[PDB]
Image (cartoon, rainbow, N blue to C red; front, side):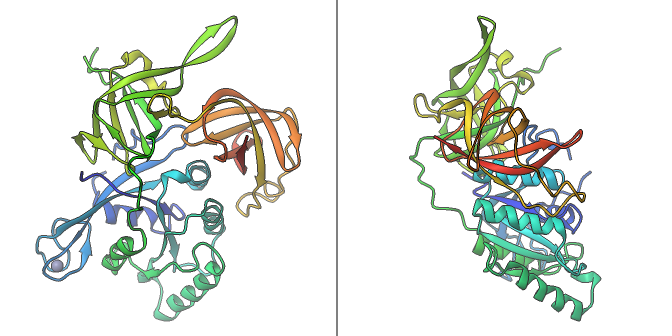
Length: 399
Ligand SMILES: [Zn+2]
């Protein structure tokens, strides 16, 4: 298996070199329709990269040809970089789907004095989800002098003290010129090693997309998602929850569906077995009508009888965010009131929630759409402040 082994979050303002850096790492330079593979509940995108090492000079890179001496490099490990369109999307992705991230690269521009508001929230989110496999990329060093670079470095050290990023390496880089990229890649190997996963645990996949690949104007329905536990294998019998909607006595219910895995695609190739890391394509025997147009997006996949429960309503222990990004009042966040209709994101699932009850640092919400989740799972909570959805906190599913 040559598929991605870890998902690495590209956490940084959408303009501190973050894009230039991601492309430098993935080697993708052609103007990118994987934009059609991105999530539509949480807008997470994946971009694989193969970490390789040069036998001649020993330096690491993500190219088959060493950028430093021109010799052929040796394969080390494939990884996948995950990102989202803009600050709000990224924050929601981290709070709702921490299990999709194994480490992160915090991009900080040395070109800028004090730690920016977005950067402050980025670290706030990493702290909340307990993601400690962090690497700090001090980008754009080619735009500032030697002294301001060292000053920025000091500010960063003070910024990370006492946080999940305290022990993270700070790597001065120039994504544009390619300076110190080899140091960053090796750091990915040293600080974001592949976790020691128990491949025997019950499989679980969070479905991001679903389609009818039948070429028209035949193949079973196809699912696209992330394996967060165990492994999947061609021929396995799988169950999908909540499942297909159906009406019963003027009410909408969901029937879990069981099917069989016909094929698996990961790392750009068909495989007989897939694991956590990167996007995984799942060919099934399902009637294509059931997966067409992302009907299964947000669903959870596992083996029959071994999936998390389905909830029609949730009791959430709520933690409101003390945000720093937004207009003057958008930061005040008024307490949650009964009858409010909130936007909830859990895993890759997305549903509106009507607040029907309140408790101490707790709310009870009736869901528009049932969700498949485990007690203890984290749920991002958003409020429609005007005409847009703004993240205001997160909840922990209570039993
Ligand atoms: Zn070399």
